[PDB]
Length: 114
Ligand SMILES: COc1cc([C@H](C)O)c(OC)cc1-c1cc(C(C)=O)n2ccccc12
Image (cartoon, rainbow, N blue to C red; front, side):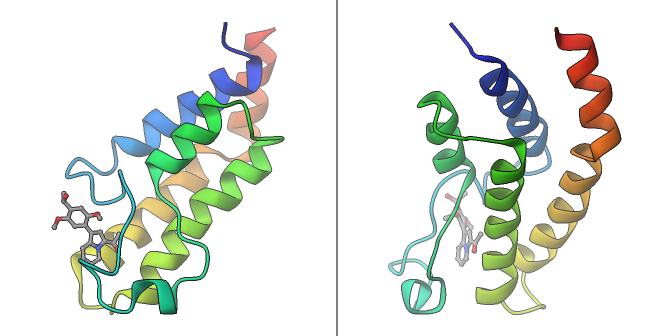
């Protein structure tokens, strides 16, 4: 049975995943496909890793989940040059996700749950 934090973060996760219809953030980037990746990016992150943390009930807060989401986007904006599809999408998704997960929207949602 889903815990309250699992419900909440799964909700956000699925909203965020719909901003990425080609699945460029669905699973991890690797050196095989992105030369130098693990030398440049210390803490890699992707929606699939976030999903496993939720399914495992390993998140302690919405803050932590937001910190992973931001990590994923910051990694994409660090590794990839401004000119690329991945940089530009990371930027839209980042802006979109912080709006979707604002304090007020989170407050409205937590009130209606329990
Ligand atoms: C690893 O995520 C990707 C997945 C796919 C397909 C949908 O499987 C993909 O196809 C063009 C690209 C990426 C991908 C994602 C990223 C990112 C997010 O940095 N990236 C950087 C350099 C080269 C590829 C990628």
